[PDB]
Image (spheres, coloured by chain):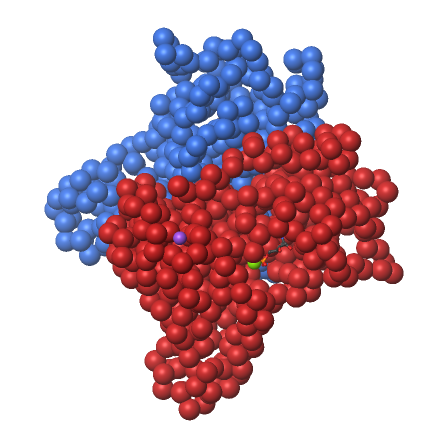
Chain colours: A blue, B red
C-alpha cells in the first residue's frame, strides 16, 4: 500500500497548532514548496545539461510572523533533523554575516536569509512542517530552501525572476550546507505545474511543460529507506571530475561535448574521467529523447531510456547501490512497468518506476517481497510549485 | 513619456477603498491577472498554431468576500465599462443557468461563473479595478476572465489543470461575449512568468518559457487609440474562412499544411481563402523561427520576422488599418528599432516594437510626431501570470 500523502490543509493545520503553542499567537503568513522526483536526466544539471523532473504532493509548509527585534526564531517539527529542533540567530547585518553551524538543518534557512536579494528584511518567527522524507533523495533540502525563500517574499517582495530565486537557494546550499548542487531541485520546487513534468535546460534555463494527462499512467516512487555514507561525500567528487573533463577538452561544460569528441580525446583525460563524462553526454541525449517520447505518449520507449539511465548511473557514473539495483530489477520483473531507475544524487534514496496504473498494486506487492530491507512507496501525480497560502 | 503602469499595491488600495464604499467592510480575498502583448504569431491560435506572447505589468485586480445569500454583487471602477458599473444577480442552480445580458461587461464574469468546473460556489461581493485599457488590444477581456476564475478558486478550489482553466475562460468568451477567440490570451494571463515570453503550441497545449533577460533590449507598445467595429464583425469571418480552407484541403487545421504544400494547392480554394491561409501557415513558421532567434539573441532576425508578420497581416489577412500601418512605418524609421507590427486582433489597438532600450525615448517622439492621431505608449517588461494576493 502507498503512503498517505497529507494535503496542504493538513500540514498547514499542524503548522498553525505548533506555532500557536510555541509563540503564543496565530501566525500571520504561510507558504508551501514541494519535493520532487527526476523522471530522467541525473548528474546533468551541474553539467549545464537537461533534466525532466516533476514536483510531488510531498511538501514543506512554513507559517510565521514578522518581528520588530531583528531576530529569527525557528521550530522544525521534522523528527529526522539534528537536535535542537529550535534555533534563534540574529539577521545578518553590514557588520556581521551569518556563518554555517549547528544544528545543521538550520544552515539551509540561514543561507537563504544571507543571500535574499531584497531589503529591508525584518526578523521573523516561523514553524516548518514537511511530508518530504529528510535524506530520501526527493529534495527535502530544496523544498525547505524554496519554502524559506517564498516566506521571505511575503515579508519583503523581491524584484527578480524565478531563475534568480532558484539560484539564491542553490547558493545557500553551496555556502551554508557545503553541497555543490546543480539547479534542478530548486527550479522544480519553484516552477512545477500540476499535471506536468518540466524539461529544464540548465544551460539556457528555458523550461518546457510536458503534459502528464493520462489516468492509465502511474509514477511509483520506491524509498529504499537506505542512506549510505557516500551522499554529500562522493557527489562533489563527481562534479569536479566532470568539470576537469570539460576544461581538458576546452569546453565550457560537458553540454558542449558529444560522445565522438570524448572517444577522440580519451588520451587527454583519466579512464574514470572518460566514464563519468560518457554517462553525462549519454544522459543529456537520453532526456531530450525521453521528453519527445513522453510528449508522443510512447511510454515503452520512455521506460527503455529510463533503464539505460540506470545502467549508465550504476556502471559509468558509479552512484547506485545494491539496494537501488535490487529495487530496479524487482520492478522490471513486474508485468505492466515501462522502466525503473534510481532518481536523485544516488547512494540511497528512491527509485522512480513508470507503469500501467492497473499494475501499481502488484508492482508494490512484488518489489517489497523481492527487497532485502523495508521499502515505502508513493503513487505521485505532478504537483504545483511554491505558493502563498492566505491565512 | 510612457504611460505610468500602476504597481499591484496601488491597485489593491484603490480596490479596497471602492469595496469599503460599496459593501461597508474590508474585502477578505484578492487576486490579479495580467493583460498581454503578442510578440509574433497572430491569428494562428484558433488555427492550432504557435504564438509567442508575454504578460504585461498592466493588470486586473479583484478583491471580494464570500456571501451567504447565494447572490453575486459586482462593481467595476473602469469608466470604459458600459452602464451600470454595478450589478447584483443570483448564482445559477440545477433548474436555471445564467444567460448573456446587460450590461455587456458583466457577461465575462457571468460566463466564468456558469462554466466554473467545481462546486459548491458561494455568492460573493467583488470590486474589479484595472490598468489594462478596455478595448485596446492588450486583452482586458482575458485579464478580467482569468482574475474572475482565480477569485472563484479562492471561494471553491478546482481540481483540474492550468490549460482547463484557460478553456473555461475561452468558453465564457465564446458563449457570453459572442467572441470566438482562440486560447492565447487566457493561457498567457495564467502562465506568464516575469522576464519570460511564452511559446504556446495551441495544438498540443505544450508551452516553453523563453527568458527575455537582455536589459539593453526593450518592448515598446503603442496604442493607436483607434478601434473600428469592422473587428467584432470580421474576426469570426476570418475564423470560418480559415476552417473552410482546411476542410477544402482535407486537413484538420492549417497547422497540418506546410507552406510549399499550400502554394501548390492554390486551385483547391478561393483566392481570398488562399491569402488568409498563406498568412496563417507562414505566421506559424515565422513564430518557430522567431522563438529560435530569441534563444540565440538574434534581435535583428526577430525584428525582420515581426515586419514580415505585419506586411502579411496587412496584405494577406487584411486585419490592419491605416493608423496601425502609419505607426509601424514610423517605428521602422527610428535607428535602434529591430522590428514593429500590429499585435492582437487587428482593426485598431496597439503595435509592439522591439528596440534598443536607449532608443525608446527617441522612438516615442518620432512615432507621435509622425502619427495623425494621439498615440499612448507603454514600456513593458515580461510580467507574472495570475496570482492570489493575501489581504
Ligand atoms: N523540513 C525540514 N526540517 C528540518 N530540516 C530539514 C527539513 N527538510 C530538509 N531538512 C534538512 O535537509 C537535509 C536533507 O537534505 P539532503 O541530504 O540533500 O537530502 P534530500 O534533499 O534528498 O532529502 C536534512 O538532513 C535536514 O538538515
Ligand atoms: N476591468 C474591467 N471592468 C469592466 N469591464 C471590463 C474590464 N476589463 C475588461 N472588460 C470588458 O471587456 C471589454 C473589452 O474586451 P475586448 O473588446 O475583447 O478588448 P481587449 O480584450 O483587447 O481589451 C470591455 O468593453 C468590457 O466589457
Ligand atoms: O541529478 C543528480 C541531482 O542530485 C542532487 O539531487 C542535486 O541536488 C541536484 O542538483 C542533482 O545534481
Ligand atoms: O492572434 C489574434 C488574437 O486575437 C484576439 O486577441 C484573440 O483574443 C486571440 O485569441 C487571438 O486569436
Ligand atoms: Mg537535497
Ligand atoms: Mg480581447
Ligand atoms: Na521487504
Ligand atoms: Na500625434
Q: Can residue B271 be seen from the camera position used here?
A: yes
Q: Can residue A306 be seen from the camera position used here?
A: no
Looking at the rendering, in which quadrant would you find the C terminus of chain B?
Answer: top right
Direction from residue A87 to residue A199 in the image, left or right: left
Where is residue B35 shown, x and y percent of the image? 53, 49
Direction from residue A266 to residue A27 in the image, left or right: right
Above or below, B49 against A359 in this view is below
Direction from residue B182 to residue B295 in the image, left or right: left
Where is residue B365 shown, x and y percent of the image? 33, 47
Which residue is outermost to the left? A267
Above or below, A343 against A64 in this view is below
In this rendered view, identify the residue nearer to me: B196 or A348. Answer: B196
* Residue at x 77%, y 44% (from the top left corner): B73
* Residue at x 42%, y 47% (from the top left corner): B377
Where is residue B145 shown, x and y percent of the image? 63, 52
Q: Quadrant of residue B304?
A: bottom left
Which residue is outermost to the bottom? B267
Where is residue B57 shown, x and y percent of the image? 49, 42
* Residue at x 51%, y 57% (from the top left corner): B137
Counting the numbered discs, the total is 0
* Residue at x 77%, y 48% (from the top left corner): B87
In this rendered view, identify the residue nearer to me: A330 or B65. Answer: B65
In this rendered view, identify the residue nearer to me: A317 or B265. Answer: B265
Looking at the rendering, in which quadrant would you find the N terminus of chain B?
Answer: top left
Amino acid at each position: 500500500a502507498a503512503l498517505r500523502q497529507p494535503q496542504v490543509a493538513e500540514l498547514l493545520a499542524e503548522a498553525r497548532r505548533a506555532f500557536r503553542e510555541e509563540f503564543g499567537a496565530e501566525p500571520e503568513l504561510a507558504v508551501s514548496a514541494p519535493g520532487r522526483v527526476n523522471l530522467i536526466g541525473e548528474h546533468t544539471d551541474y553539467n549545464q545539461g537537461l533534466v525532466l523532473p516533476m514536483a510531488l504532493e510531498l511538501m514543506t509548509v512554513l507559517v510565521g510572523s514578522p518581528r520588530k527585534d531583528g531576530l529569527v526564531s525557528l521550530l522544525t517539527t521534522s523528527e529526522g533533523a539534528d537536535e535542537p529542533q529550535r534555533l534563534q540567530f540574529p539577521l545578518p547585518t553590514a557588520q556581521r554575516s551569518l556563518e554555517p553551524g549547528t544544528p545543521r538543518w538550520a544552515n539551509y534557512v540561514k543561507g537563504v536569509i544571507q543571500y535574499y536579494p531584497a531589503a529591508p528584511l525584518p526578523g521573523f518567527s516561523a514553524v516548518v512542517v514537511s511530508s518530504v522524507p529528510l535524506g530520501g533523495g526527493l529534495s527535502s533540502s530544496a523544498s525547505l530552501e524554496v519554502a524559506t525563500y517564498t516566506f521571505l517574499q511575503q515579508l519583503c517582495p523581491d524584484s527578480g525572476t524565478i531563475a534568480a530565486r532558484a539560484q539564491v537557494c542553490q547558493q545557500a546550499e553551496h555556502s551554508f550546507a557545503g553541497m555543490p548542487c546543480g539547479i534542478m531541485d530548486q527550479f522544480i520546487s519553484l516552477m512545477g505545474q500540476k499535471g506536468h513534468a518540466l524539461l529544464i535546460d540548465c544551460r539556457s534555463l528555458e523550461t518546457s511543460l510536458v503534459p502528464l494527462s493520462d489516468p492509465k499512467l502511474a509514477v511509483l516512487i520506491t524509498n529504499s529507506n537506505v542512506r549510505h555514507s557516500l551522499a554529500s561525500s562522493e557527489y562533489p567528487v563527481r562534479r569536479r571530475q566532470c568539470e576537469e573533463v570539460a576544461r581538458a577538452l576546452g569546453a565550457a561544460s560537458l553540454r558542449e561535448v558529444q560522445l565522438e569528441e570524448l572517444e577522440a580525446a580519451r588520451d587527454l583525460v583519466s579512464k574514470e574521467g572518460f566514464r563519468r563524462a560518457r554517462h553525462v553526454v549519454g544522459e543529456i541525449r537520453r532526456t531530450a529523447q525521453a521528453a519527445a517520447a513522453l510528449r508522443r505518449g510512447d511510454y515503452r520507449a520512455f521506460g527503455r531510456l529510463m533503464v539505460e539511465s540506470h545502467r549508465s548511473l550504476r556502471d559509468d557514473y558509479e552512484v547506485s547501490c545494491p539496494e537501488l539495483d535490487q529495487l530496479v530489477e524487482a520492478a522490471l520483473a513486474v508485468p505492466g512497468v515501462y522502466g525503473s531507475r534510481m532518481t536523485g544524487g544516488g547512494f540511497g534514496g528512491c527509485t522512480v518506476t513508470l507503469l500501467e496504473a492497473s499494475a501499481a498494486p502488484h508492482a508494490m506487492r512484488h518489489i517489497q517481497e523481492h527487497y532485502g530491507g523495508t521499502a515505502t512507496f508513493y503513487l505521485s501525480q505532478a504537483a504545483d510549485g511554491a505558493k502563498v497560502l492566505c491565512l
